[PDB]
Image (cartoon, rainbow, N blue to C red; front, side, top):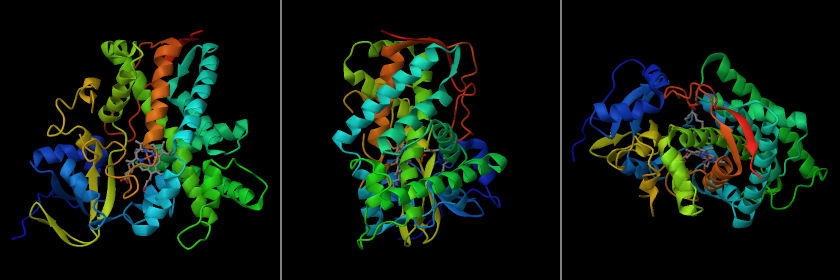
Length: 417
Ligand code: HEM
Ligand SMILES: CCCCCCCCCCCCCC(=O)O
């Protein structure tokens, strides 16, 4: 059939509009163009942006889209690391992804939840002897201690503080400009070298992590040819566990926000029926902004909706806008856990990617995230009391990630006993 012209945003480069609008950039234009797909110019080149469940399923078609060389270098050097799983395609990707999925078994997730609970207890005891407590910063430290213990990474106290700062900077810098962006580049450089040394100690026999742990599994994994991963690559992969675990602190912020803003939803949790906590956690992941979009390159020319996708074109999948799509969800722009009662598809609810864990790039740590969020919600509701003082809890849709301006201050913390 005839090739049609995709809706097109004019201007020599539109990256500035993405920087100004953030999470809302793609959905605003899906609305104004009356199309789930449009073309623009971002980072000096043509770009295609698309959202909704059909677009998501097409984006996850690995005959049509590849990840090699898709992410901008500025994102590789902050968020991802070079030559990690995010960069791979085909059987090489499948085999690397199996390494990540191998640490996600029932017994290992139980180990994670036990650690997470203990580290919450430790933090709460500390906060009870404090006055004001900055939840985002304290939660990053909870999650850094949890990550290192679960991963088998030995850390001294000074190393905990430094890692918490540097892992934070890696994700807080990825969509930043200027001075702030470079903090994350330097943070990544420092921890890559530190983790590389540690992996060399594992391989030399001088450190002996338990067999079940990330550090053991990633240090000893062999590729499709039977060879150990390069030390640099294995370090990037370990950081691809430690960093996103720290990042759960962003979702902890939003759990606390939701408990403060929605007392009727909090009261439904006081029952002990786990269905309510499950719905609440899912709705936090659906409603609040976090990972805006993912990127791929067109692998081979193809047609969809009458439009030509040309090989090599950078393509953005709108995660935020799909999670807020009024063609998928009833009243998408309100927080309503009841929408999940006995719950859509793997392409419609995509805060941590869509599709299949093994056949695509969907987040390896989605179950970790959900389980950590459940522990955190249980702590904040059932194991402590605190006050939320008057403060600026607003969160900007132009900042990625989006953090409430006050960083969520709590006070008068008391552990229930
Ligand atoms: C804290 C909140 C998190 C969010 C919002 C999040 C979101 C995402 C998204 C959107 C992707 C990319 C999907 C794609 O490329 O198609 C991804 C990939 C990934 N995530 Fe997460 N994630 C989080 C936590 C975690 C955790 C806790 C872990 C590890 C325990 C983790 C490990 C990974 C890995 C290894 C990948 C790359 C998978 C691949 O390329 O095949 N993430 N995540
Ligand atoms: C490829 C688009 C980059 C988007 C900008 C990053 C803002 C969100 C931070 C996401 C962190 C998710 C977990 C992680 O990978 O550490």
